[PDB]
Length: 99
Length: 38
Length: 38
Image (tube, rainbow over all chains, first blue to last red):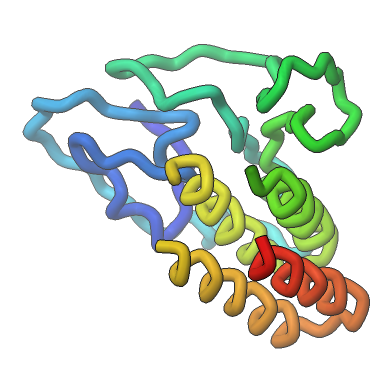
């Protein structure tokens, strides 16, 4: 498995290690004794002015299941408010804009 | 609970990545994670 | 916990002032004065 993770959050990849930037869109179940390597990708994969290329739903109703990975256009909810893009107090479209 | 605060700090994230200093938005993001877990 | 939250948004104010925009700074100061009462 390969994915984007920022620098000072790299260490968060651990069994039973939840989080915000490391959990809401990825999770490893317990019992994997292996290796992960992180490194700078800016010598080729970066650009000045905001690298408008990455995204992950910054809100979700819970964590992820063992190695769960499910796409979702669904908004986050506190109440039951039907919102399809309009920013209310609980509409909360989880689009986190990595530029 | 603090839905006012949640809406306001989400607005802050919006404006903050609408700034250029894209980094404190993500900090506030983990802060909201902290609110939700608490 | 509660003081961690108040001081992380303390730092929110601090950092945003370290960025520089009178408007958003006023807004988040309103935010902290609102939260500490709530």
